[PDB]
Amino acid sequence: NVETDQQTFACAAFNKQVAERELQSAYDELIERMRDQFGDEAGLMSRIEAAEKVWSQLRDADCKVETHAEQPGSNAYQIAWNSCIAQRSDERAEYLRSLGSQN
Amino acid sequence: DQQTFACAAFNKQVAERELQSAYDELIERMRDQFGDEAGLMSRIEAAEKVWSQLRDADCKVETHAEQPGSNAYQIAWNSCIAQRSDERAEYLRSLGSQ
Amino acid sequence: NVETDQQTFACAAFNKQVAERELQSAYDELIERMRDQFGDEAGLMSRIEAAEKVWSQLRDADCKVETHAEQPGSNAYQIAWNSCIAQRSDERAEYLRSLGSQN
Amino acid sequence: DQQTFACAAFNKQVAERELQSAYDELIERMRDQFGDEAGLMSRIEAAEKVWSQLRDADCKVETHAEQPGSNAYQIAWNSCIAQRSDERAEYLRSLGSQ
């Protein structure tokens, strides 16, 4: 199934792109929300950018664990990798949305 | 310990206060953005009611190995409720962010 | 974009099905893990089934809030609905996996 | 309150103990299922190290409105660490479940 089905493969790649675009939108909107509540507060935007950088490193480290049993480059590996990236990105997007609403 | 017991109870209270604040601020955000949109307040209220039912059902699963009415069960129950509440608060804060 | 693109629409529906199948697998495996650690403990499997039932009700209630600004039946609504179902299902699957590992 | 301060600190300790247990049990599950698979223990260790760096970076964002070194900042810091730890523990428990 995942080892051979074109739509499973194509949609895993496609949904990773959608999840990444939605995360970028969430990040961009958090910056604007934080600026609305706090102005360009000293260190704030740099701290948000630094955290997001470390997050992207974690995302990749965790996806290397989650996909450890799959063969790099295989259909199954790409689907697993892409699903992991999408899910992790969705969860990060939710977290960034939640931060803008801390009053 | 009296202290494990007291802190588990206190931290549940704190988590529920923050959840209530997240809920109230969501309602205000939604009204700000969408006004008296038909059904909107009612959908949010209904969802949160079902959530509290899930919270108790999941906590009954998580505490299954403890003896109900025991101090240990109550610590475990409070800890589960607190964590579930924190997760729900994050989710409500994430809603109506556009 | 989401209002008109076929692949966005098709992959949102497809990934909802994948997420639901993965959740069912996680649920089925939790039952087996709980049985391995505790046997058919009085009330345990019924409590797990009851919780999952309420969860499915919550999933739908929450997705009705998340999609409130979209028009029922529209491309945008279906994509939003399906993405919400998929994300909620992924998060539930992770939670059920985590429960089997509570020692 | 001395009690808010003490419970926030205590609950951080509890959350970190449960996270360490989740981490240790994950390692045991992984060894049970995959043996000395090349790179596997090292990948899990490396990921958890990066996670602790993210935890501190995100907590610095969450506590940005408080004065560092203040009792209020430390309560807020401990609460953030505890919740982040609980979330990580759930995630590690979810790994190697097949």
Image: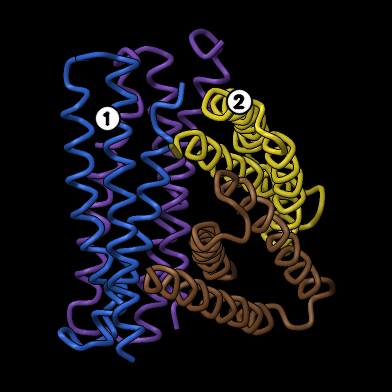
Chain colours: A yellow, B blue, C purple, D brown
Q: Chain of mark 1?
A: B
Q: Is residue B38 left or right of residue C67?
A: left
A36 with respect to B18 (left or right): right
- Residue A21 visible? The answer is no
Residue pictured at 26% horizontal, 86% vertical: B66
Q: Quadrant of the C terminus of chain D?
A: bottom right
The total of numbered circles placed on residues is 2
Q: Residue furthest top?
A: C4
Q: Quadrant of residue D33?
A: bottom right
**In the structure shown, which secondary structural element does the residue marked by tag 1 occupy?**
helix
- In this rendering, the answer to whether C72 lies above or below D19 is above
Instruction: Please state the horizontal and vertical placement of residue B24, each as a whole percent of the image.
Output: 27, 36
Residue B27 is marked as 1
x%, y% of residue C81?
38, 28
Compute the Cα span from label 1 to label 2. 24 Å
Using the image as rendered, state which of residue C73 and residue A28 is in the foreground: A28
- Residue furthest right as drawn: D38
Which residue sits at x=29%, y=26%? B28
Dot 2 lies on which element? Answer: loop
Are dots 1 and 2 on a single chain? no
Q: Residue at x 17, y 37 (%)?
A: B46
> Three-letter amino acid code at disc 1?
Ile
Closer mark to the observer between disc 1 and disc 2 = 2
C33 is higher (above) or lower (below) than D92: below
Residue picked out by circle 2: A39
